[PDB]
Length: 53
Length: 53
Length: 53
Ligand SMILES: [Cl-]
Image 1 (cartoon, rainbow over the protein chains, first blue to last red):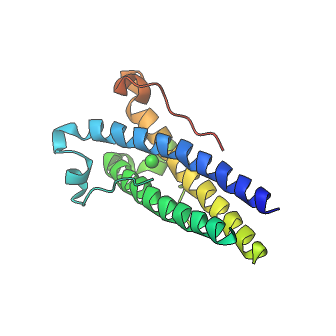
Image 2 (cartoon, rainbow over the protein chains, first blue to last red):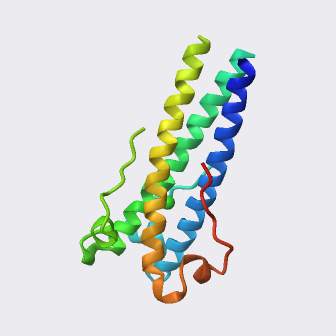
């Protein structure tokens, strides 16, 4: 029962790891589409958001 | 031990918050790339997906 | 108390589901922006990342 809660958290951690690989690959695609404009953040006029695990 | 499970859930919540900042900044980049076409959802011919915390 | 930890994990699972809908719609937008170049992965020269729930 406490083991079942721990297994759900491990599954959920593997899911977030998978999803973050999709997100960061999307970010690299946007960095390439915005190469001539100074990059994604410079074009939005925003501070860049980075992912911390 | 129950405290260790609670700490893992708090770490995991801080991670998802960080990742969602990257995702929403990517969405704003796509909204700008698709400005002339009526926006990302109008160009996909989809209902827009929004993030609910 | 164990029920409160389980409720937090269910809320967190609903959040990740919501966020993944935003991420995959962003991926479909990038697939369309990169249609002429062979697709997002072919343009990055990367193996494609996919999301596994
Ligand atoms: Cl994304």
